[PDB]
Image (tube, rainbow over all chains, first blue to last red; front, top):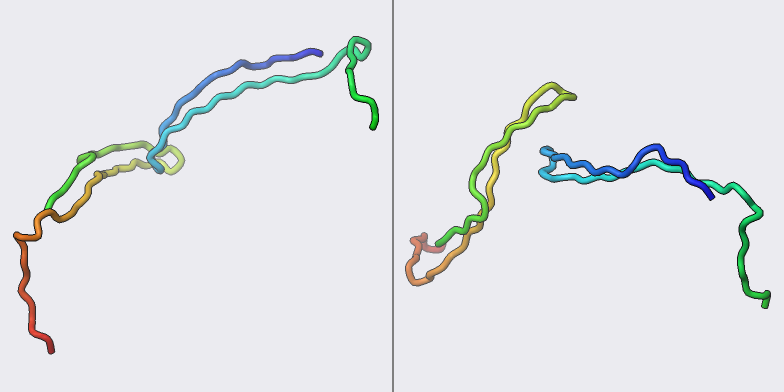
Length: 48
Length: 48
């Protein structure tokens, strides 16, 4: 399994005057996938 | 009678960029009530 990164975590603050409030936000961007099917497995329960 | 203040009068300004203007605001917070019933009265009219 592999991962590709474009951006990292960040925080930001802002103020609103039409509603008398405050704001906080965080964000990033990533992607995931699988590479080799011959290096994986699982253990399960037998059918009832 | 009495009065209780939590915040006092204040003013504030802002800038709007999507309508090309400015804003001005004023605000406060208060509450009112009565304390002593032995120092009050009223004058009225006779019925009918």
